[PDB]
Image 1: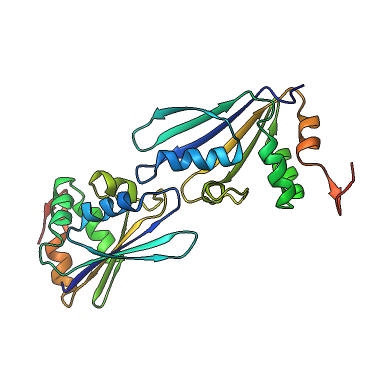
Image 2 (image 1 turned 180 degrees about the vertical axis):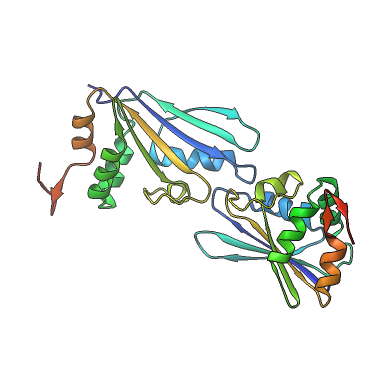
Length: 137
Length: 134
């Protein structure tokens, strides 16, 4: 059964940007998003949402294959408040399909918000603490 | 002036044609070269046309920003070179904004001129409450 209620991904789309390319960057990280877009004049807010229990599978895989479980876990923990876990990733690196937590993204990070009633279990499943691949928690 | 050169980065989520549009909104008649740097492309435009600064001349006056423009030209000035940085997204809609936290980097305009004092005085005369004092 599901480990989260919903995933919401948010990014700003600037006038010199392509809304389609920003949608692609978001889907690279969380597949199957349903988009709404909101006009703010100086940019558009793109919001992606999914309640699909398999929505975190791409992150699960990228954290492991990039070998960034330690950084991923630190970022999840920093973003953990109440019933939400929020991370911010590099927009341009997401467009080429990887995760980068460097907060200095040509303009605007992509923000990923995970709404969950079991955040300790989510974080331990998504970004386990390991030593040479061996569980240390 | 002898030349106007204009530079901007094009990031992967950007459309090069939109960045070109923004540059041309500010300095018409530019010829471009593009340089791939991987994480972004560098776009560089150029023109020697003597009407190359009329849009800026006009926009500085129309937007009533003669004070900020002169201050930015002076800050950017030495010798035969005046460099200013303008907001890319505002340039895309056709205006000048000298606020430098520009989404996806600024557009950098270089004016090359043998007579930069005459240049600054003509383009953005010193003003008091908007009223030119020279």
